[PDB]
Image (spheres, rainbow, N blue to C red):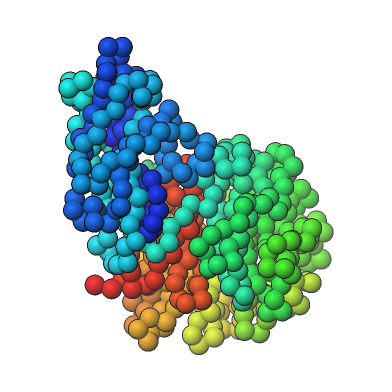
């Protein structure tokens, strides 16, 4: 009879309730004759000052996230603990054979958000009728306080086993749109059966509407996913996504197709999806130079609408069946989405790529590094004719890319034009989701700041009206899509 212990490392926000600090698992139910179990724990004053109440939670489930995040799919009992106390006890008849125990807290109304605000606790002893059990730590507890923190899509939500692939969008009217792959049966990509789902917020991300499936997968080989979002200059919302067979299964005559859909009511309703594959490649393509290309997909997340009105996304395109590599081209529209063209090639052996507007009006491309090329660094390219043509810009390199989709934001910080870039820190793996600041004038990257430790993958980033960063990340091995709000001073001041 051993006891295994996991401290929580997920972010918190003020006034949240029943946040797990430490969870422990009995390897066996309490034996008959056992009457009581007692849990002694430690918790520093700095954490105690940040909480308003403590709890012992007991459940038949051993869950990854805070138990309220499973919205009742996890049932549990809650016994309060005085925040000044350091032990609690419960009869074996109350535990009722259950094996999983949580030390949880209600977060106070803290108002600091510096890097120092880290909550922690640790279980020191689990005793059954006075007989202390052996406890082994698999994880330490450290939960950082952010101005906002909320899991928008959690495994099991609405009957979908999994979620992946975040996209976020802020509209000129302040509406936030959050979309995701609804991965119904497992976490793998197309050709699995996948839907596109969405939640909206009309109060700057304080609260979100219930998820609505806006594009429905119709079976294996007939799913949809990899959403990217823009707002066009005329005000209509534009989403772009792929559907069908997997990327490497696509062919010119049986392609994984690219679709667009639009919204003229702040993301409440969306037009029926429109196949635009024929503009890009394949059997219906008017350019015979691309008749025999095999596959294309736009990087999920956000595109870019230029000052001219031109709408753009970077497609990553498979041109040859003899290799498993992709080339980047800009997919753009000068007519509010009515028609679409391709730029000249922007990057050889690229992958998911993102655009942002340089302070001089040039366009910067950030290209995912696939296959651990070169020094395993993020790739960059520049365009000075609004996306039509491109050249490598090593001058922007200098951050590691373990091979993952990220996002850029052009921000002004202490009077300096800078670029915020989100990527897993790694190294060489999907761990510790971070952001970096690139100072434009010096051409120097900051040191990374880890927003979310642990398993971390795709991220997308939006700038809120007052300059708070909205950061939408894939958290965990079984991924949750988590919306985090912070200001740049919270992460980069000393
Ligand atoms: O996988 C998970 C789920 O949240 C955790 O184990 C954590 O993200 C990482 O794996 C280690 O901290």
Of residues 475 and 52, the one nearer the viewer is: 52
Of residues 469 and 384, the one nearer the viewer is: 469
Of residues 120 and 80, the one nearer the viewer is: 80
Q: Position of residue 35 (x, y in %)?
A: 27, 18
Q: Position of residue 457 (x, y in %)?
A: 46, 53
Asked if one can make out residue 22 in the rendered structure from this viewpoint, the answer is no
Q: Which residue occupies 62% across, 80% down?
A: 306
Q: Which residue occupies 47% across, 33% down?
A: 75
Above or below, comparing residue 280 to residue 384 in the picture: above
Above or below, comparing residue 181 to residue 67 in the picture: below
Q: Quadrant of residue 229?
A: bottom right
- Quadrant (top left, top right, bottom left, bottom right) of the N terminus: top left
Asked if one can make out residue 138 in the rendered structure from this viewpoint, the answer is yes
Q: Which residue occupies 77% across, 58% down?
A: 273
Q: Which residue occupies 43% across, 28% down?
A: 60
Q: How many marks?
A: 0
* Left or right relative to 61: residue 38: left
* Left or right relative to 363: residue 62: left
Q: Position of residue 358 (x, y in %)?
A: 50, 81
Q: Position of residue 48 (x, y in %)?
A: 23, 52
- Quadrant (top left, top right, bottom left, bottom right) of the C terminus: bottom left
Q: Quadrant of residue 208?
A: bottom right
Above or below, comparing residue 128 to residue 245 in the picture: above
Quadrant containing ligand 1: top left
Of residues 153 and 69, the one nearer the viewer is: 69
């Amino acid at each position: 009879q051993e006891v295994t212990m996991w401290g929580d490392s997920h972010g918190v926000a003020p006034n949240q309730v029943r946040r797990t600090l430490v969870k422990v698992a009995l390897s066996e139910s309490l034996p008959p004759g056992a009457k009581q179990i007692r849990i002694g724990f430690s918790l520093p004053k700095e954490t105690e000052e940040k909480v308003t109440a403590l709890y012992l939670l007991v459940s038949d489930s051993l869950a990854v996230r805070d138990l309220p995040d499973y919205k009742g799919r996890v049932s549990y009992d809650s016994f309060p603990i005085s925040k000044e106390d350091r032990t609690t006890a419960l009869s074996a008849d109350s535990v009722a054979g259950r094996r999983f125990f949580y030390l949880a807290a209600d977060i106070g109304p803290v108002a600091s958000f510096s890097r120092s605000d880290t909550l922690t606790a640790r279980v020191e002893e689990v005793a059954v009728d006075g007989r202390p059990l052996p406890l082994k730590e698999l994880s330490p507890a450290s939960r950082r306080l952010y101005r906002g923190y909320e899991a928008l899509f959690v495994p099991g939500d609405g009957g979908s086993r999994n979620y992946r692939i975040p996209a976020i969008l802020k509209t000129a009217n302040g509406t936030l749109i959050a979309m995701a792959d609804r991965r119904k049966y497992n976490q793998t990509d197309l050709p699995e059966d996948i839907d596109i789902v969405m939640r909206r917020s009309t109060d700057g991300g304080k609260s979100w509407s219930d998820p609505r499936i806006i594009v429905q997968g119709e079976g294996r080989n007939h799913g949809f996913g990899d959403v990217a979002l823009v707002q066009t200059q005329a005000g209509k919302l534009l989403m772009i996504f792929v559907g069908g067979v997997g990327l490497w299964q696509s062919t010119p005559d049986r392609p994984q197709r690219t679709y667009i859909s639009e919204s003229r009511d702040e993301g409440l309703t969306w037009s029926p999806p429109r196949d635009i594959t024929h503009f890009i490649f394949g059997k219906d393509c008017a350019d015979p130079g691309r008749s025999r290309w095999l596959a294309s997909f736009c990087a999920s997340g956000q595109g870019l609408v230029l000052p001219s009105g031109r709408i753009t996304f970077v497609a990553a395109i498979r041109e040859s069946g003899q290799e498993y590599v992709l080339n980047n081209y800009v997919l753009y529209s000068d007519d509010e989405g009515d028609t679409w063209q391709l730029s000249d090639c922007a990057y050889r052996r690229g992958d998911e790529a993102k655009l942002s507007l340089m302070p001089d009006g040039r366009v910067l491309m950030s290209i995912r590094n696939q296959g651990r090329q070169e020094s395993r660094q993020r790739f960059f390219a520049l365009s000075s004719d609004d996306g039509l043509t491109w050249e490598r810009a090593k001058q922007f390199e200098g951050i590691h890319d373990p091979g993952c989709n990220g996002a850029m934001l052009q921000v002004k910080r202490n009077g300096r034009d800078q670029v915020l870039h989100s990527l897993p820190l790694g190294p060489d793996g999907r761990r510790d989701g971070a952001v970096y600041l690139f100072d434009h004038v010096s051409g120097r990257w900051s040191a990374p700041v880890v927003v979310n430790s642990g398993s971390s993958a795709y991220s997308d980033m939006t700038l809120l009206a007052d300059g708070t960063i909205g950061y939408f990340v894939e958290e965990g091995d079984e991924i949750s899509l988590v919306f985090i709000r912070f200001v740049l001073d919270d992460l980069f001041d000393v």
